[PDB]
Image 1: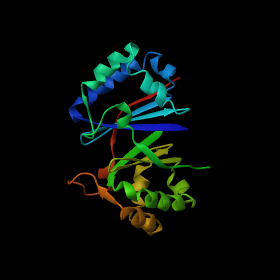
Image 2: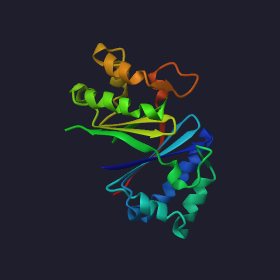
Image 3: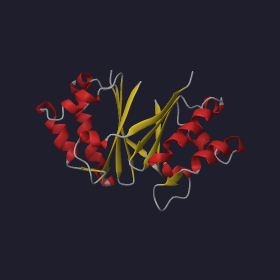
Image 4: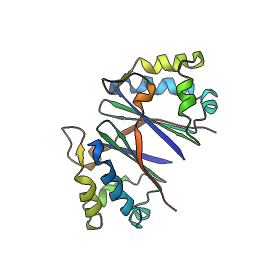
Length: 106
Length: 106
């Protein structure tokens, strides 16, 4: 039921690296830990969008674990190819979009 | 298993209208028809992102039904508040992002 979407800028050509970095991380239990159930990466022009599906608002641990050594790697890894969308960005929480509507059919 | 994400530009302030337009459309069977299982709208700065979850690649009917009178309304409705992201846009398919990675945990 929980969905979050983060948006950054990326060179389209860097997608494969990006994908590769997660691929590896997603083989470990690091994510089942944080509580991630599904992960989808999209690209559109020079925008990168990371969709996370979970079972609860897991953002906090998410935010928590970034400073974390267990996650430096995936972070460096991914990080070298991503840039914050907006000029006023200070932290991770800043790349998170807002949901303003949600509908599930019966 | 099917996920698509469309991105356009929107004035943050127009969100409530946007939401209202779908709210109504989502009360009808019009979407259960097209095959939509879940719908989530996000906003980030002046970007609008529409996530559709389905059970198959439903984009074609999706694309099909736009010219459609059954869908003029929601379309006009929504449409007046959205603008194509990129300058080279010619059609709806052009607002669709690409998935470059997908992971589901066991």
